[PDB]
Structure formats: C-alpha cells, structure tokens
Length: 141
Length: 141
Length: 146
Length: 146
Ligand code: HEM
Ligand code: HEM
Ligand code: HEM
Ligand code: HEM
Ligand SMILES: C[C@H](Oc1cc2cc(F)ccc2nc1N)c1[nH]c(=O)ccc1-n1cccn1
Ligand SMILES: C[C@H](Oc1cc2cc(F)ccc2nc1N)c1[nH]c(=O)ccc1-n1cccn1
Image (cartoon, rainbow over all chains, first blue to last red; front, side):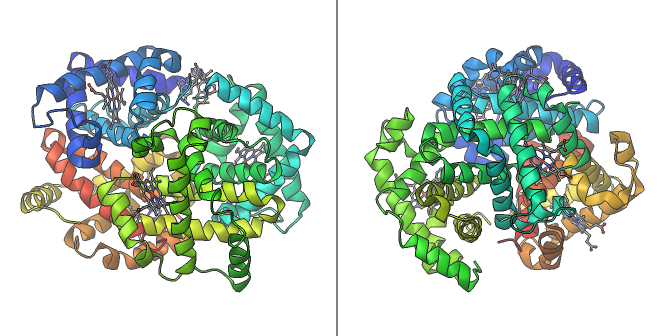
C-alpha cells in the first residue's frame, strides 16, 4: 500500500529517468538475466546476447509500462489489466521473478541516478515495484 | 488483487463462520503459538496457557477486524488504517508472521467448516488474507 | 527433525489413517488452484483452467499420490531428511528450477488437507508436530540450492 | 560459492575501493528505512523514526561496519562460508530468531549500495558475481535453521 509521499517520490525519481527509460529497462533485464539465470527460462525465444536489439526493444516496453503505472498509480488493476492477463493468466510467472527484476531496476537507478536514489526514494520505489508486481501476478478478472 | 468471484467467496465463507468468529480467531492464535513458537515474542504480556481468557479475548478482536475487512473489502487501506498503524508503525511485526497466522486461520476453517472449504474458497480466502496482511504491514498513513 | 515421543506417536497414528488415493491429489490440486503460477510446471497435465478441471484431473491425482509417498518417505527418515531427498532436491533445483518458497507452500497446503480430512482430530499439538515435519521436508528439498 | 577467475578479479578490485566507514552503515541504514520491521531488532540504537535519523545514527554506522566486515570475511572464504559463519549463524538463528528472508534483503540492499557508490563501474557482470556472493552469505547465515 503506497502513501501520498511514496507516489510523489516515485513520480520525481521516474520523471528524472525521462527519455532514457528504455535504456534503464534494457539494463535491468540484462542485469536480471546475468545475475539470476533461471529468469532466462521465460524468454527462450529471445536473442539474449549482449546489446541484443530484442532485449533493448523489450526494455523499452517494460519501462513504458512502468511510466503508465506511475501515471495511473491509484488505478493500477484497471490500467495494467492487459499486463496481468499476460503475466498471471498466460505466462504464469512465478512471483519470485518480479522481486528479481524489481531489485535489478533499483540497482540500475542507484548506479545511474545517485543524487535521486536517497533512502526515502529507494523505500518508495521498492514499495511501488512490489505493488506493480502484485497486480501483474494476480488473477483478478 | 481480488477478483469479483473472490469477494463473493470470502463474503459467503466468512458469513458461515457467524457466531463462531471469536472461537476460530482464538483457535488460529493457539495453532500459531504452538506451531511457530517465535510468534510468541510479540505477546510477552499475554497469559498463553491453553484456554486463557486473554487468548480468547484477543481471538474475538482479530476475528472482528476480519469481519470489518470483509464489510469494507474494496476500501481496506482506509478501513484498517488504525490496525496498519499498530502492526506496521508501533509493533513492527515481521510480515512472515502474517503468513503464519493466515495459514493457521485456513487450517481452523478447513477443520471446522469442511463443506465451505472448497478449493475455490480456499484460494479466495488465501488471497483475501494476503491483501489484509499487505494492508496491516504497510506504512501508508 | 526432532519430534517428542508423544508427537511421533500422534503423527504416526494419524498418518496411518490417511486416504492414499485422495490426500496427495487434493494437496497438489489445491497448490495449483491457490497458487496458480505453480501450474506452469505441469503443462503436460492438460486442462488446469478451472478448480473442477484441476481436482478431477487424473495426472494431478497420480502425481499427488507420488508427492504423498515422498512425505511418507520423510516420516520414515526424520533423522536423515537431507540424504533421503538428495535425488529429489537435484530434480527440483537443477532441472525444474522450482523456487524453494513453493516447497513451503505445498507443505502448508498438505497441512490444510490433513485438517480438512481429520477435522477436530487435527488438534493444535498434532498440527505443530506436522509443521515440524513439513518444514524439514521443504528444507531437505531446498538443500541442493544451499 | 564459485566465482570465475575474471569474476574473482573484478569482485576483489571493486571491494578494495569500498569506503569501510560508509558502505556498511548505508546498507544497514537502508535495510532499516526500506524494510521497517527490521528496526524491531535494534531498539538499543534509539531514534530510528526518520530516514535522516537512521542514516546519521552512530550505532547504525558502527554496526554496519561490523556487517561489512563479515561480508569481507565471506569474500575471503567463498569455499567455506558455512564453517566461517557457524557462530554468526547460531547468533542470528538460535539467539535472535531473525527470519531468513531478512538475510536475503540485507544482501540485496548491500548490492544497491555498491551500485550507488560505483555507478557505471558496477556493471551487470560485476553485479552477477556480487549476487553469487551475497546469496552465499545469506545462505550461511540461515544454515543453523536448516
Ligand atoms: C515490473 C515488472 C514487469 C513489467 C512492468 C513487465 C512488462 C511487460 C510488458 C509491457 C510486456 C510486453 C507486452 C506486450 O507486448 O504488449 C511484457 C512481456 C513479457 N514479460 Fe514482462 N514485465 C514485468 C516483469 C516480468 C518478469 C519478472 C518476467 C519473467 C521473469 C516477465 C516475462 C515477460 C515475458 C516472457 C513476456 C513476453 C515477451 C515477448 O514475447 O515479447 N515480465 N512484460
Ligand atoms: C489477519 C491478521 C491480523 C489481524 C486482523 C490482527 C488484528 C488485531 C487487532 C484487531 C488487534 C487489537 C487492536 C486493538 O486493541 O484495538 C491486534 C493486536 C495485536 N496484534 Fe494483531 N492482527 C493480525 C495479525 C497479527 C500478527 C501476525 C501478529 C504477530 C505475530 C500480531 C500481533 C498483535 C499484537 C502483539 C497486538 C497487541 C495485542 C494487545 O496488547 O492487546 N497481529 N491485532
Ligand atoms: C515440498 C514438496 C514436494 C515434494 C515432496 C515433491 C515430490 C515429488 C516427487 C516424488 C516427484 C516424482 C519424481 C520422480 O518420478 O522421480 C516430483 C516431481 C515433480 N515435482 Fe515435486 N515435489 C514437491 C514440490 C514441488 C513443487 C512446489 C513443484 C512445482 C511448483 C513441484 C514440481 C514437480 C514437477 C514439475 C515434477 C516432475 C513431474 C513430471 O514428470 O511431469 N514439486 N515431485
Ligand atoms: C545476511 C547479512 C548479515 C550479516 C553478515 C550480519 C552480520 C552481523 C555481525 C558481524 C554481527 C556482530 C556479531 C558480533 O558481535 O560479533 C551482527 C549482529 C547482529 N545482527 Fe546481523 N547480520 C546480517 C543480517 C542481519 C539481519 C537481517 C538482522 C535483523 C533484521 C540482523 C540483526 C542483528 C542483531 C540484532 C545483532 C546483534 C547487535 C547488538 O549487539 O545489539 N543481522 N550481525
Ligand atoms: C487506490 C488504492 O486502493 C487500494 C489499494 C490496495 C492495496 C492493497 F495491497 C490491498 C488492498 C487495496 N485496496 C485498495 N482500495 C490505494 N488506496 C489507498 O487508500 C492508499 C493507497 C492506495 N494505493 C495505490 C497504489 C497502491 N496502493
Ligand atoms: C478497490 C481495489 O483497488 C486497488 C487494489 C489494489 C491492490 C494491490 F495489490 C495493488 C494496487 C491496488 N490498487 C487499487 N486501486 C481493487 N480494485 C480492482 O480494480 C480490483 C480489485 C481490487 N481489490 C479489492 C481488494 C483487493 N483488491
């Protein structure tokens, strides 16, 4: 459950990512595949070599979904319903994987936006990613 | 995230508990204290002997909070705000303990209401208890 | 796993009354219904789209009976759970990549099923002894990850 | 924990540049801010009511330095983490009763802190090597439960 300050902290941090959102998304996926190789089992159809266009393209989709989640932070089940259909109903992604990707996104933000990655902002982003994760892994239709 | 069927299943199942709400609450706590002794650390001030009036009294409060959660299932952060402040801010309950109590409540319902404890209802109650748990362990103020 | 002599007696007596054709299939079936991502590991079972399809699926029933057999093997080797489940741990980790939290979930679903079948006889002290058993089994299954 | 020679070199080189007075305190401080129930284990530290109170608390800084020392010891004994941390595991498991999930959380917060300090130098392959390390340390701290 997000507080009003958490929503503001996430909007500020994610806003600072701006146009490089896709780059952060791609790096988080690369970090996830290398750090937690079991996550690759969900992407057998991907070229997962370093600098692969497929990982870059997917990174942009993930990052754009997060931008959409921020923009509809109080209406996430309705706004992310298509992504829950995909991850919970079709792919049946084990929720542990969402904790792994969430951690890799936090790492990416800590490495590239150090001035923005304060302890308060780290706390708000971790809660935000856990809420987005609950929505994507739950069957609510 | 709860589906419309989950809400209906929870309202029906929790409605069948009726007058026994407090008894189920007390038994779930007893099961938790015996099965997971680390949970006793949160209750040093309680008489935890079998059939203790304090455990019976607390069991009724827990069960009544759950009845209130069912009655406000789509507005739980607002309706449970005082319980969230108690468990997350004051008591600092590790979230693992909520998984333990939730499991002991499911065990109690399975043992005493077998006709109601269908796989669909077990799934809906488990999701409901996880949503209540997220609210009680989050600081959203 | 250390059980007191009274715990060992109560666990053995209850276990001897377990319906071998139902309990395992019901625990596996409930794992699939309650924690739906576990269905990803059982795509060869066919239709798992509804609770009724899961509970009446003969592959769920037969596999559930094998799972019950492994918990039973655990009860016969409480002093050597790691060794007893070594081959199973390698299968679940190295080959299937089953996250260990799912082992804890199945153990607890099995406890819910035992409560469902035994009712008032599945007392809080009986449950406590079974929780020691299922935690030891989940830990042994997760040993090859450690 | 097995690291490749290239991983061992990159892990050692980065670790040698770690500010011993800051990194540990920042990882512990962030654990307390991000996962607030962990504050229950540190009531003797006094004021932990705000992120600024946590981060500037000298008991958080001193304890964090001890935590960093234990991770540093882990890096020197990757082939014997369980034996090296046997006493530390008895303290956390038998005396403190820290739920093991919290050990994984601290390891990951430490990874976030290393990324925060090293920026672009904390590359995805460098992170991967550090994830193997922190998983091993967390597993050794939880071994007395197993
Ligand atoms: C913050 C968490 C996540 C978000 C916001 C997210 C978002 C997305 C989006 C937007 C798509 C594309 C859907 C489309 O084409 O319209 C997608 C696809 C997918 N996601 Fe996720 N995802 C997340 C986590 C995960 C995780 C943790 C896994 C597995 C480890 C995963 C596996 C997949 C797979 C396999 C696909 C299909 C890719 C393809 O065939 O093109 N996702 N995800
Ligand atoms: C479904 C989950 C839970 C619910 C609905 C719940 C509900 C409640 C309620 C209604 C109270 C009384 C507040 C008052 O006096 O106005 C309370 C107190 C408390 N709860 Fe919970 N609780 C839950 C889980 C837990 C868990 C998992 C723990 C720890 C293992 C816990 C520890 C406490 C403690 C220590 C108190 C204070 C008791 C006293 O001094 O009287 N609760 N809880
Ligand atoms: C902790 C409790 C568990 C026990 C005791 C257990 C036991 C077993 C046993 C005895 C087998 C048969 C091995 C054989 O034929 O040689 C098996 C197979 C398997 N288990 Fe488990 N298991 C457990 C948990 C899980 C969980 C949580 C999952 C997945 C979410 C899982 C997925 C599988 C799969 C996919 C197979 C292979 C089935 C096939 O041949 O198609 N198991 N398990
Ligand atoms: C996995 C990472 C961890 C490592 C390497 C670690 C390491 C240490 C070390 C080296 C000590 C000092 C022991 C001594 O006196 O020699 C310590 C003490 C302690 N640790 Fe940990 N720890 C970890 C995780 C945790 C977690 C997650 C918690 C609680 C949530 C925790 C709570 C404590 C407490 C309460 C003490 C005693 C402090 C006091 O004296 O007041 N530790 N830890
Ligand atoms: C709009 C949203 O509604 C709910 C969030 C829920 C989260 C749960 F984990 C369980 C039940 C919930 N029920 C809600 N009605 C909400 N409402 C609030 O009063 C406070 C924060 C908030 N929030 C936004 C994003 C994440 N939380
Ligand atoms: C009213 C509630 O609003 C939210 C629930 C949220 C739960 C989260 F885990 C994260 C974010 C949430 N955001 C909400 N707006 C809601 N809305 C729905 O469209 C579907 C189910 C549902 N629900 C009721 C009880 C539990 N879920």
